[PDB]
Structures are given as structure tokens and as C-alpha cells.
Image (cartoon, rainbow, N blue to C red; front, side):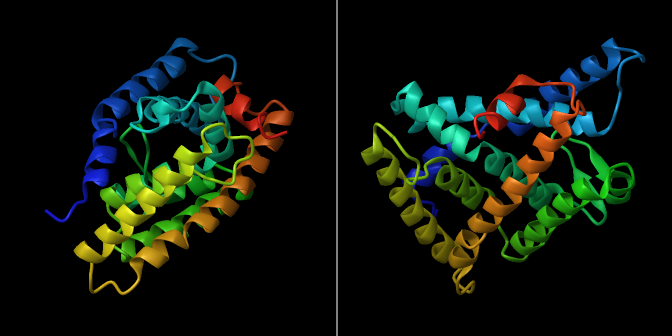
Length: 242
């Protein structure tokens, strides 16, 4: 039905969103229920709490992923360390495209929060990053960015060839080229009037890149003086940078 085979397989590797939301929702209700006051029941750390969970879900996704699983643990870690924050932001952006509304932000827990509530209860620094992400959301919404293009961008983000010291480089470049091809074939077969949405889509990766670094720098800063609880997947990957 105009969906190449390679894409049908990537989609099969996607987690069922509803159960990921339920699992994350519970975790946060626990983390927030268990300590029932005294310590730090913040709002910055909470977005940090669900970002951490989202990250674990992303790592599991990559691991169970059709082509990633053929790489040795050494190659896997180097690909995930290089793009983990980009994957997180891309995940957020797509969730806004498929579920976002008027003046709300759809959270991974499956909840809608007023964009005003987020802004007000967070410092301007975080505010700017959140706003830089919505611009991309606005651009993807116009292009009719859909799920099949979303899993393709994910694999293009994960399988990046300019990562140094990859053992099975032949496989990483192969998949990358193969996904690029399946994506172009899909975009013009399903959105032909869209002169170059394919180009538009790829032009988004460098932007995701830039936003990604600014996000890590802010995350590191907030971390250096004790403003996040801790959360080892977030910190671990952030320290894979230094």
C-alpha cells in the first residue's frame, strides 16, 4: 500500500505507545507517591524523571531493533552515546506532532499540560529549548510528518556513519543508506504534491543536532549544582560526552 518493506519492518520494532505511557505514569506516581513530602518534589526534576524513563525505553527499543541487534555491544554503545539526546528530543517533537493541541504539550505519561503552565513554572533557559522544539513541531506539522517518516528519522539518527571507531561500519553505512532510500521512496509515493518534504525532513536533523547540544549543556549545568535527583541513564550518557 505504498510502504516499502524496509519501513514495514522498522515499524514492527516500534513499542506500543499506550503501555509505555502506563508504565511511565505508574513509575512517576510511585516516585512522587513514595516520598510524600520532605526531600524535593520539584517540577524540573520531574521532567527529568520522565526523560530518564523515556531514555530507558529508547535504549530497549534500539537493542531489540532489527539491525542494531547485529552490532557488538561496543558498536551499540558508541551509536547510542552519540545520539541519545537527539533521539529524546525527536521523540518529544513527534509526540507533539501526532498528539499536541492548541496550547498544550503532550507528555510521555500520556497527559496534556498547558503550555503556559510549563513556561511559568520553569526558568527562561528551559523555556527557550522547549520553544526551539515547538518550532520544529510547527514545521513538521505543516509537512504532514507521519509515523513512517518518524521511524525512518530515528534510524537515520541512530545509524550515523561519522562515529569514530565503529567495528561493523559496513553495516551502519548500509542501513543508513538503505533507510534514506526507503524514506525518499515513501515520501514522494505518499505525498507527491509535497515537492520536497524529503529534503525538508532531512534539513531538520541538523536543527535537532543543535537543539540537542544546548539541551545537554543546560542539563549538565543544572546537574553540576545538584538540581536534578540523579537518574543514572541521563547522567551516564551526559558524562559519556565529557
